[PDB]
Amino acid sequence: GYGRVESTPPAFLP
Amino acid sequence: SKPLKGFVICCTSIDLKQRTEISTKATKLGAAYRSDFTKDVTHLIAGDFDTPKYKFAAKSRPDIKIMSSEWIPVLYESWVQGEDLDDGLLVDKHLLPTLFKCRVCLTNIGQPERSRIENYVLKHGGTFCPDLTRDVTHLIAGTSSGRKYEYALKWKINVVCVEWLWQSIQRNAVLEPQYFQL
């Protein structure tokens, strides 16, 4: 989003 | 009757009108007011963690209590209203939250550590931010990579490792980011 980096989806977490 | 006899109070990042009100009321309550952060200071009333005074207390004064801006106005009102004042003098109730004004975002941290960190942030008075926005004060990063990492740097947001959080919680105050760089 504008001025926003959305939360990493759980399936993509290390 | 001087409920705050022996208390030495200093203020940091407090509105001029509210700071004048606090210096007056604390003096009436029997406390010693300090404009400068002198050696005899026992309590620091803070409006922000990003000040030389707050940073000095957090780094060099673990004996002092960091207080909310509401402590003196609330205690003074209670006193003049004839309300009962205990040995506590509303200090425990008006202790500034450990992560006061912290807006904490995470990147490259897996589960269940992500949930654990969120719970400790909320517990110690911080705001947990699933999304990175320009109002985030701290980005806890597992690795120095990804979109959140890259934008936090562009937006001049603190990029720290998880020890920033754990050491701040243990100190019971917000610590500086330069010691917790990735």
Image (cartoon, grey):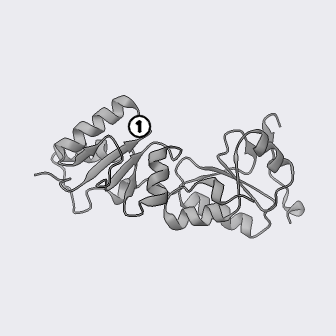
Front residue of this view, candidates B51 and B108: B51
Please state the horizontal and vertical placement of residue B125, each as a whole percent of the image.
53, 55
Left or right? Give the position of B32 relative to B116.
left
Front residue of this view, candidates B97 and B160: B160
Examine the rendering and report whether any part of residue B81 can be seen.
no
Examine the rendering and report whether any part of residue B112 can be seen.
yes
Q: Is residue B140 above or below residue B18?
A: below
Name the residue at 48% across, 55% down: B97
How many numbered marks have been drawn onto this rendered protein structure?
1
**Most extreme residue toward the bottom, as rendered?**
B112
Name the residue at 74% across, 39% down: B155
> Could you say which quadrant of the image residue B133 lies in?
top right
Q: Chain of mark 1?
A: B
Q: Which residue matches tag 1?
A: B14
**Most extreme residue toward the left, as rendered?**
B1
Question: At numbered mark 1, what does the secondary structure look like: helix, strand or loop?
Answer: loop
Query: What amino acid is labelled 1 in the image?
Result: Ile
**Most extreme residue toward the right, as rendered?**
A12
Name the residue at 64% across, 46% down: B137
Please state the horizontal and vertical placement of residue B8, each as a whole percent of the image.
26, 52
Quadrant position of the C terminus of chain B in the picture: bottom right
Please state the horizontal and vertical placement of residue B14, each as a whole percent of the image.
41, 37
Please state the horizontal and vertical placement of residue B39, each as a whole percent of the image.
32, 54
